[PDB]
Image 1: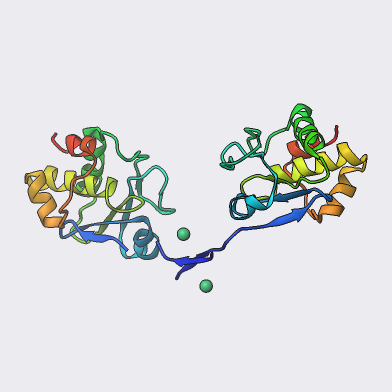
Image 2 (image 1 turned 135 degrees about the vertical axis):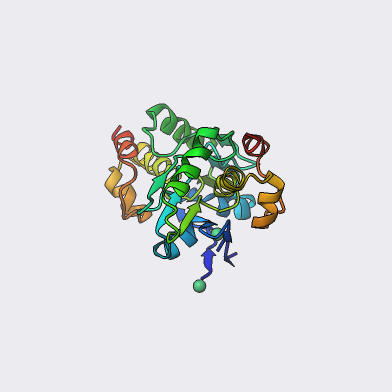
Length: 131
Length: 132
Ligand code: NI
Ligand code: NI
């Protein structure tokens, strides 16, 4: 018999950085000076920075540092940054946590608390966040 | 904004003794048939009398078309109904049904399509396979 069903994530990271899913980034990307796509399969058409990142795998520190460096070096006190993946639960949350850790010298727990992340990412992503 | 997952259950008459369908029809009406023939790898009827592990969108070797034609001819005792099904009922089971009609009745692919009301081209490699 016929079935009728339906199947947007955005979180503030700090004063200057937001984290989202692809849907939010497409609909609201123009509200940001810089869009950072950290999913291989969800590359914003006007992404300033794209890391072709697979999900559910260990993320090397050099990727975390590339994104942190990108934000810090373009932080002119007037710029807003959006980090997004596809569903906005795994890859963009990890890069966002890593940015907070690298920039403010806080723990992974404290980063999550600030962003309101109350879950565990893929074991291998959580491992990657202990740099 | 919501979306719909419509029901299948599509069935075409092939000849006096043979019907062609999607998996949904085969599941819900299988018991109305003496012999269910499954010609999809991934849609094997739990009471299939014959199963060909056929992938879609590929050349079908003559050997397979002949296996199905022979199976129906051999079990055609004047008292038996046959159902040939794949998954969506538009490609693999249509190709095997067309090949059965060509082999048994010496008509053309185009005439077999006409009888069955097939107003479309199958995958190019399937169309190649039907020109035996
Ligand atoms: Ni759906
Ligand atoms: Ni509707």
